[PDB]
Image 1 (cartoon, helix red, strand yellow):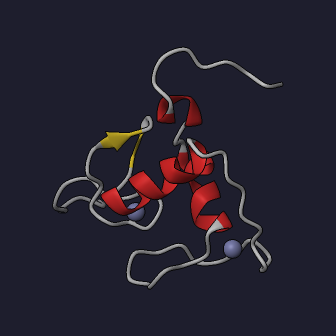
Image 2 (cartoon, rainbow, N blue to C red; image 1 turned 30 degrees about the vertical axis):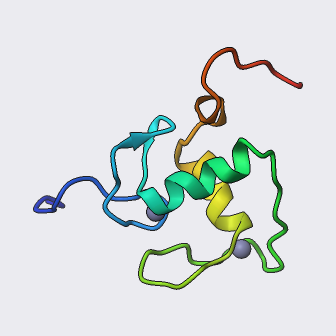
Length: 89
Ligand SMILES: [Zn+2]
Ligand SMILES: [Zn+2]
């Protein structure tokens, strides 16, 4: 009985997802935040116990946690880069 909403929500922060991005439904805020890191191959180090609350009603939250949450919820990196997607083991 969890119905009655306005469109899809961001599985990362909850923000109204702007459509299925990277295989998963994520908002525009995380949509870019995920790529900018994926396409760039970045890697943040959560100074915390990787338990930072990645919500929407919260200013710039953790980076590693927020970014990771993507690979957790479902967001796939392969997508970030269209075309052939090789594997570096
Ligand atoms: Zn989001
Ligand atoms: Zn964190």
